[PDB]
Amino acid sequence: PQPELSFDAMTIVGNLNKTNAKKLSDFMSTEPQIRLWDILQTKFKAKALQEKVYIEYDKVKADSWDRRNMRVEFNPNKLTHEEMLWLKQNIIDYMEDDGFTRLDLAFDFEDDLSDYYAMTDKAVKKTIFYGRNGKPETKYFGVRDSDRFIRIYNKKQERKDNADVEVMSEHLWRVEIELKRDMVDYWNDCFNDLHILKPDWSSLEKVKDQAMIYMLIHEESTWGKLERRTKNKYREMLKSISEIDLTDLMKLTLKENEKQLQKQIEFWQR
Amino acid sequence: PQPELSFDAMTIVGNLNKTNAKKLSDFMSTEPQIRLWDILQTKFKAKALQEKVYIEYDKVKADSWDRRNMRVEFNPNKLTHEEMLWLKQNIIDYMEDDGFTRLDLAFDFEDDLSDYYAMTDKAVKKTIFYGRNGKPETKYFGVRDSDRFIRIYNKKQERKDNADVEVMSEHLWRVEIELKRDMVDYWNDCFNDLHILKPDWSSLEKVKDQAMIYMLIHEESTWGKLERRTKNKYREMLKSISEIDLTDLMKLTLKENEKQLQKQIEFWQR
Image (cartoon, rainbow over all chains, first blue to last red; front, top):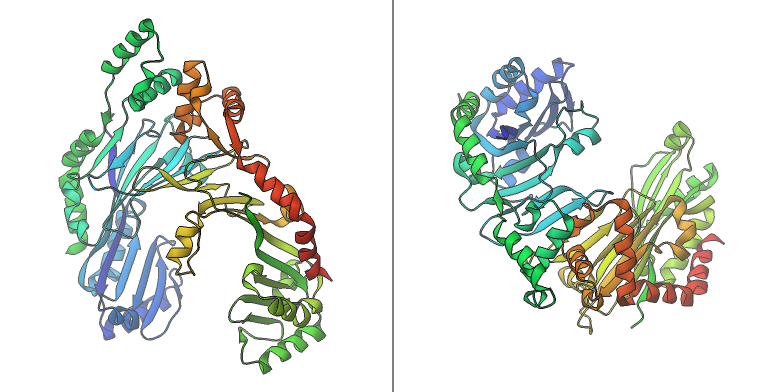
């Protein structure tokens, strides 16, 4: 099946006037439905819309690193058009120099992705979190502080664990691609380095089968131990087997929704 | 070789008199070499001995929730006996209802553990950090917020990275066992489910067996694919195949030093 694609995180960074800092800082105090803390003249923190939007202004720490001075963080999937409108008009518009610092692509699949893994053509570090059952629930590829980082994890299990409403499907895995800094401008075709795979052996139904192959694939000597009637069974099986690459479906769904997603971005920049 | 064993973290929780709170609060203000903050009559925070001991008193929280009102945190390995003496006499003695809330066992080995297979018989979450190499570097069994949590990792590499004094040995790996809450009283046998092995699948004369193992020891996920009754068969087999199990050396060193360590604890309680 084709995976559903959406943006799942947007950070927007800008710069805010001395005038506007106060103005905005003043505005927000008057609204009890927004929560303010860690206030000074150069600093302000806030969550808005039932805690769905984080907002941080810091002048003293913006300039100390020569950067822009205000972040706004939120998940667009969790905002209602009304809300999106509210946030743009009452916050984003008063920012200048504004662009995207973070942007996350979320591909939901109704298959089981436990055995899938990402590779860039560059050699990267991996982390896998296994459940009590011994199965893998979350996978990290690369590092979170970088232009591109990929999670592959059991959304169903994670939603269940998060006490979210239960879901009709028997399997649900996400592939999140966190694009930061300069990579955000390439979101619309990011897959040149990257492939999301599942091995040869993984595709078999039978644990003993998949072990036996894996061994044959990794220790040449293993053929020498095996009887001829057996050798043929596994020669058959080897040829019968292909590695799977979801990349292609992803690129497809991406292309299919490029224009909507693109508009959905442009919304914030006007 | 036998691994050196030591405690690598202690917290101690207690209650402090109105009289002693002040007495102690008074004492600390006079000493410039201790850093005091967040002070009231019912509150204080402090770091002492060149920032190596954290100390926190809160009465109003303690009254608000029916709890003990003071914690003292430190690593005993990083204290000099002189220092240990100072802390007991000038702080701990003045506590009552005092016991241990955290206790960490650190087994250092001069072998390379990369080449062992580490496993718990118990069903708990595993985290494995893989290197760019594809091989596993660090393993966590359990979660940090729990009665018992285990790290296995390259101490030499971690010490080097930490700009610590270099070490004569070519290899140095730690096995840290963080015991919290009620588990602290069972420090003398907290790792019996844990096994660290060196199996050679080859010596199994049956061939599906050897594949299955080889896979288990090279793809952690494949435990997830085994029904519960099967997992035990292969756990049996693993242990049955390895001449070496470092667990045994740990249990030994532990027994050998149980009495000293025990005294080293009793030191704090008098």
